[PDB]
Length: 263
Ligand SMILES: [Cl-]
Image (tube, rainbow, N blue to C red):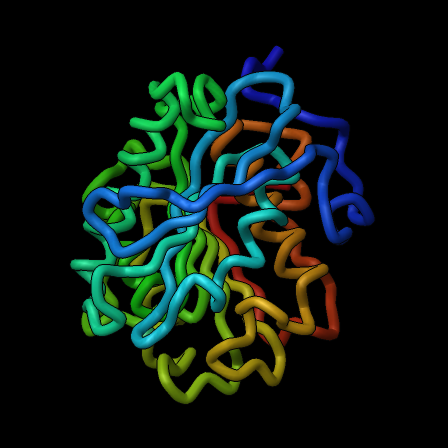
């Protein structure tokens, strides 16, 4: 019996819906430590400690670009911190540092009796997500910190595509028509570089660079996949093996690839 399993048995429908089982609240971090600003989203009623995920935007972008993930993930049983970077013009390595600073601060607040998330986090179970350079920053975080349980960047941008050292389970969301971080020269070579992990490549048909951002038209699919990946790998929750590993057989997806990921 898995000590990290939370919530009811999943269905496609429950994972495609606006929200999972748990009530979500949020708060602004009053004194961000090592990054620009943060919002923490958390379940009030998960039934046990949950893992933490830190989410970073792209170059020029702010929390609004990626924060639809906050309630979506938190409602399925995660503490989620969405950040602004110290500068909108921070590069990937800096973004990685800031992402891990955010995780650190979540751990601090877990141990702070006045915090809404006092005692709600399992600080041994953490994941990383982010858009574009924030996606590159997530992969750098995974490479440098292999104790992370999951990595799920979207439209990742990085000046080097070789992430062959990564042992963290990694789901790459790619946007087919991305002109900023082109699938063929960024997301795909990243994906292909990783031979040591569970990994997945999901390309959204016709997607611009912002295809997985807040307000996108594919929240059912993208949120199903993001939540299933985090549940399978952050919580070791094999109820989610099929959702995490399966080809979703969607006309919204124009390329699907996965490895070391059994349904
Ligand atoms: Cl970017």
